[PDB]
Amino acid sequence: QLILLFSRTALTEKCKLEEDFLYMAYADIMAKSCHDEEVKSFEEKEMEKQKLLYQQARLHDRGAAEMVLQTISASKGETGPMVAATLKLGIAILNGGNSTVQQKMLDYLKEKKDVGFFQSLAGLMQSCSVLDLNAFERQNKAEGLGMVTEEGSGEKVLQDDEFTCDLFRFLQLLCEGHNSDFQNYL
Amino acid sequence: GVEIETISPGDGRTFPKKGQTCVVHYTGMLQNGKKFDSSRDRNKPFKFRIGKQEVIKGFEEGAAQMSLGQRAKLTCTPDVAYGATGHPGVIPPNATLIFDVELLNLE
Amino acid sequence: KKSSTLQQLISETMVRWAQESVIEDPELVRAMFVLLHRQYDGIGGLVRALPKTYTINGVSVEDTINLLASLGQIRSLLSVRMGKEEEKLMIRGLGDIMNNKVFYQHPNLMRALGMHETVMEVMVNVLGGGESKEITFPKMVANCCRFLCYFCRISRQNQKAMFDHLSYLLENSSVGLASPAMRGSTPLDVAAASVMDNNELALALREPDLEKVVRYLAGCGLQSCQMLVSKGYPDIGWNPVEGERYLDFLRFAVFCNGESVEE
Amino acid sequence: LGVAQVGRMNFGKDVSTLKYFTICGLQEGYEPFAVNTNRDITMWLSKRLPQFLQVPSNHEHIEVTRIDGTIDSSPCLKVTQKSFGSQNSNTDIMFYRLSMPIECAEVFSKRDDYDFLMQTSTYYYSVRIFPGQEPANVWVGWITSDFHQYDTGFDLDRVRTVTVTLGDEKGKVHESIKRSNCYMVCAGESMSPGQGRNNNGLEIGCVVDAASGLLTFIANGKELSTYYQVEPSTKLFPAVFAQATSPNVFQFELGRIKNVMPLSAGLFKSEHKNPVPQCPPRLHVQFLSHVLWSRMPNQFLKVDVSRISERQGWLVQCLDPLQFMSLHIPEENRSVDILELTEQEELLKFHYHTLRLYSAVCALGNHRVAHALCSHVDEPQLLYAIENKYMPGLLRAGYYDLLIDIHLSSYATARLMMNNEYIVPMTEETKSITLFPDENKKHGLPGIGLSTSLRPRMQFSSPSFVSISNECYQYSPEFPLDILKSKTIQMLTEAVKEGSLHARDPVGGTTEFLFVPLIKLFYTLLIMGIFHNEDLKHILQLIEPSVFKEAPKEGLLQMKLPEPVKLQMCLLLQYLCDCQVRHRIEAIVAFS
Amino acid sequence: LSKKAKASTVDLPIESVSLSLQDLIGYFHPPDEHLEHEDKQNRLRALKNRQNLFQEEGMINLVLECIDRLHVYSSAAHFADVAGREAGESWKSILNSLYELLAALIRGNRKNCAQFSGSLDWLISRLERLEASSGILEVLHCVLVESPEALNIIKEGHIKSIISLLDKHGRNHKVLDVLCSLCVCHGVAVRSNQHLICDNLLPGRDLLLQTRLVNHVSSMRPNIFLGVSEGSAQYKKWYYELMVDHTEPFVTAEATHLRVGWASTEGYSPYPGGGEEWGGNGVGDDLFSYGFDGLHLWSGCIARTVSSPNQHLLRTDDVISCCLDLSAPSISFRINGQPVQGMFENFNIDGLFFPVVSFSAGIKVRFLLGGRHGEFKFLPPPGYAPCYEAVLPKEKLKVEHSREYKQERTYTRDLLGPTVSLTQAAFTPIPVDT
């Protein structure tokens, strides 16, 4: 029911994807539940793979793979916390190259003939940030003059390095395992 | 001005003076007979001072002629009460108000 | 048996409802899961509540109550459309709040209550109302701009908080520059005060924001003043009255504390 | 029931009272009609006294045609019989009236000129008896709302009348006033010249002077000797009584004559100064009929009658108060019980939307409009509406919303909009606060405790319309909050047990109508914080007995409730969690 | 056609326009509720795109021009005279279809409703017409609901026309809904509109139904049924007294009701006539009853003030004596032995009269019917006979409810049908002519 509510909200026609705290919290919960994370035995690794498969099935059997695509499509290429949470959820359900999730996503995209998904994917790539030498120089001068910057990490330079990594890891997981069908679809 | 018709008799000796509070129950009715105000509905007596222009002059002059414990009918012409502009939302313009007033106590 | 806790009672009840019936009401589903998430994430309630917690001395209780009442009166103006009767309420509330001592003594409680957003949003609702029709109720907008300038001048942290809302004020910056006797009481003045005499904020100021102001200045140099020519002023190709305001803003942006910001 | 017949109906509300149910009806699975009911069933009877209602479009005797008035012809209403001539036709006298009355002045004073028409208060309508309808079977004139007389044989002598004669102490009659419900003339006697109908159908003219109360009739251009003088403030309904001897009976002409203002000016206030005659859609022909139902009151006055003794006579004693809320139709000058709207759908819908308009005009802190609305919807009427069990669900919800918006919404919003902030003063009361009530780590009841955080101030203004001071407009009108608190607690307590039995007759007709308004009022009171200590303890026990036991009944959380009520319960549980968060913040400050 | 023109030379595509309007309405029909969420969203998106395309191509102004051009003719008969019989027949349908199409084109779209703000004033100018009132009101409702800007155009002259629509056209809840939408839109309240609606609609108390709490009023009467008729053995003068042992002026917010006098029955039935059974009506609230409250004379629900020594509303320890003379119709009252300076005269006597008292909660009254039952405190006026003398020999005098239904158990309640005419009250001796 929660997954259906979140999917219906995404499918609802809106000019902009409004920020929803309920989604931003439950998507994080559902993403953490999937992963739940010196040589290890083969039996132990096999057990850990089967546990991850079960934890991913518990969510993609209820429609999370069709939710993460709908939210990204409704984002309309606007970077935000909702998109970041959706990408994290997609990565969590797609870890290990889950063939079932890949097939469900490809089938859903093909049957819906969704163009907004790919348009939003292009928009997010265009909106992704890079190194900004001007901002770096301004921060260096501000620190040198004597006042301390409110952020010690210089977060203004390279605005979102986690969002870009998640966005490209999602697309790599989508094609992992030499999934030729989705590789050609992209 | 205002007519006073006595509904119930009073003591006939104690009248309000200047600088004294009048405690009354009143029931406001229009000429057509529709109620618009009643202190008994709110179950609280109404207190006002004579000569301080805290009430409409028709009500004031009508209650000034009453005695302690008297119940009387006060008919205020549209000139002593809310003039011609009326009270917005309650009293229509150029309306005559009939009041059933009982003087409880002078304090 | 007994859950013995409100948290446990809610956590059991809401899941029980969801598993008993397929709820058709999205509002009910959303409220249900919001409540369940709140029960499970107890520490998040404190994480959200503590930043909104302020501590005052006993002697300032009455003044704080008066300030909170005035804040409530100003906040309630957000749910009503702007008018003549509401203008007086807004002005009186703003005057009382500036006269109150807590406004100066506790700027952190000021920023936590966050009137620097409430005044902005009221003002910009007014500006959007009749935008092409040119600003109506100009005196309240002037009062709001003066209040925001004073809020900036009270503390350096308040100036930084105001700096966050810098770009938006600069789209809403062509309102009353031409209007005389409005000087020092415009959103452009608020923007200038947001970056006045602060090296950190001057350096944090971005390039597209300056590009927008330069574009406004170029437009003012290319085109005349419609309001002045409507009032009957002799038509000239350019607009000195409008241009000088943007020039002063650029002066405040580039020059700070006697030195010059090279960037 | 026939003539001189006495009967009794037993709905089996108490199964023991059914005499033959066990011998025949219990084993077969049949159930008493009122088996699962807590309140008595309302019975409706046939009305003895006829009333005036609009002629139905499907009436099999009467047909009404609305003729729009041209530039040269006045608007007309035309009354015909469709079933005339054929078998089952109606030979009895039919009483017709117009739906809107003319208002006589409160105090009696003591080319047509445009100024004269603007200053005059004299109105006119004419009735054209069609050539062929015998004028001796047609009467024309005015009637009042008191007219409920249905006689197969009507005559002007039989009309009800009385002559109140007031005199001085000596006894001389210093005024004599005649009062009657019918002021009408007969066309047969009105045709004074004779043969006036034959060449052209009689146009009986009715002239009323609202400034003097003088009713004058003109037939064929000559003023008849018959005239009437009515009391001030009298409401006169245009009316025509006719026995039809023809398929076409008569016509209602809404025209005007020389120096006389048209009738649409006296009927409608918007057209008070419009000499052009008009027939707006509100005006329509009504007829007197017996097809109406009457609702028997659930409770009657308790009156004790007994003969005290030989000398003292018979004693009549009534001591307990009983009241009912009455709906008044302004145009028809009629009043009916509001509980009669359970079968009148159009009035119910219009009044529900009127209540919504009342709640909307005072929405979002319009304190002046709330003060004005206190005159129209009073405190006793709100309390009776809240308490009443037989009220329709729509009106129940509307009156609950009206009470909340007029008296409570302002402060409820004021406290809600300052909820997620915690300004706690530094006093000894704050220092005394601790996370747990005692050494045992057992959570206290939510809400109950000592809260020192600063909270908005509650202020109210007394609604009075005899005070010229305008400073009363700020602050919402005052209400008896303690009485409302006790009522809400009592009715929640009753509804918890009533709903649990799953009775077939919930208050308002549905579980939603029973619970949503009452729980909404409870939530508003809780938000405003009127509930203190023991009241909160009792209502928390009502919400959930086992969990909130202080240290067999099922609380609201376990009664299988509808979704709208579940949403309100979610709101209440949210408020309790907010109270716990505030207590935690205060304890943290105390430790700090 | 408007320019003088020869009718048949003008080619007016009535059927094509009607069919195109019917197709356009289906082309803009809103999605059905029972459809699935995704399908409903798709249909809504398609509808929004269609509305945007139509508004960008300016199909709103064309519909407005057609409506304005069709309103030049007052009625269907006028349009038929100008153009032709089929055109006159289809005129009303075309207007309704055009208004429905406009409502469908602007419904749910904020940009279209914002663009309709300028034409709002033109639309309200024909709200009074019965030819287009419903469609104009629906368009107004959609525009006001969907456009925050639209409310700023509505002025006092536009609000008063909508209010007067209620007066002219009668009660209609859609007008109330439009007035509600005027006050608050999207959670924002327009205080000027609220004040205008209140000040222009509420004080009249002539359109909206009014409410008030009324005390229940019941009536007690003796058994006697006395009347006057030709050739009857009934004495024409009667007299009885009522004593008030205790009365409470205000048992509730409303004043206590206490009226005494005589009442009559319609015809020879034993049922009181002309009055309702249960409610707030008492003695003197109809033209069949005659009352006295101590200060006024009540008849037909109009009260006239009557003078008396030391006038007061009926109090504790007050003796009211009632006199009825049927020889010349006259009802007179005497309070505490002093005469009340007023009387009822010349009323209908084609019925049976009986003593009656009406009251509400908080009384304690006593019938002094004279003789064995009661003892008169004051000597009856000469000629008048006491009321106990009218009891039939086999009957026993008692005070019972005026109306047949009283307070009792439901299953024990005696439902009563119509009662036979009580002709035995007037004993008219009619020997057979011989």
Image (cartoon, coloured by chain):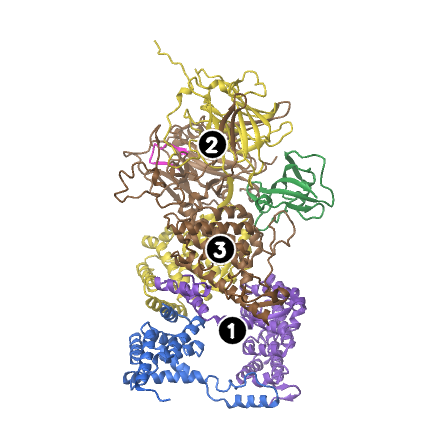
Chain colours: A blue, B green, C purple, D brown, E yellow
| Amino acid, disc 3 | Ile
Determine whether B89 is above or below D301 in the image.
Answer: below
Q: Residues within 10 Å of mark 2 (few under 14, many from 20)?
A: many
Spot occupied by residue E349 in the image (x, y as percentages of width and height): 47, 23
Which residue is the site of mark 2?
D182
Residue situated in front as seen by the camera: C45 or E183: C45
Q: Tell me the subunit letter for badge 1.
A: C
Query: Which residue in the protein does label 1 denote?
Result: C47
Tell me the distance, in whole angstroms, between the alpha carbons under discs 2 and 3.
60 Å
Q: Is residue D254 above or below residue E337?
A: below
D45 or C31, which lies in front? Answer: C31
Chain ID for label 2? D
Callout 2: helix, strand or loop?
strand
Given this view, does label 2 or label 3 mark the residue nearer the observer?
Answer: 3
Magenta stretch encompasses residue E342 = no
Query: In this picture, which residue range is highlighted in magenta?
Result: D241-250
Left or right: B41 with respect to D145?
Answer: right
What is the number of the mark on residue B13? none
Real-space CA distance between mark 2 and mark 1, rounded to the nearest whole angstrom: 80 Å
Closer to the eye: label 2 or 1: 1
Q: Residues within 10 Å of mark 1 (few under 14, many from 20)?
A: few
Chain-order first, disc 2 or disc 3: 2
